[PDB]
Amino acid sequence: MEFVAKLFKFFKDLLGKFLGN
Amino acid sequence: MEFVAKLFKFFKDLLGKFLGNN
Amino acid sequence: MEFVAKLFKFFKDLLGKFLGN
Amino acid sequence: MEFVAKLFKFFKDLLGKFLGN
Image (cartoon, rainbow over all chains, first blue to last red; front, side):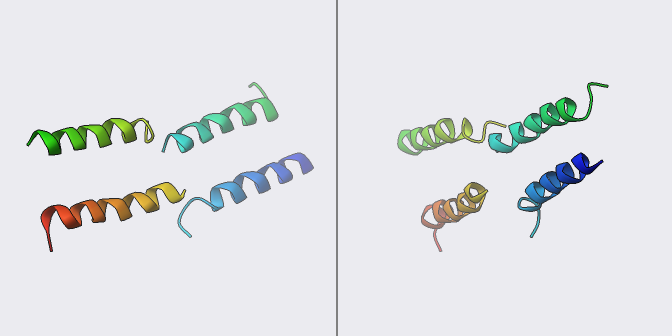
């Protein structure tokens, strides 16, 4: 499961730099 | 932007390759 | 006139490929 | 990214000296 924890961290952080801030 | 239009297109490749084909 | 038409044409052709969505 | 943010800066510029003040 630790894999997906790293995965989401990459996903949500990347999109985070993109949407409304 | 086309840059985005392919970013997700790149994600779909990663995820399907990362978690499982099905 | 032809000038403005040509200028807009040039801008759109050069830039639409960039925003090639 | 910064492209779109710059784009509107160009649009308002284009519109500025096009239509007037």
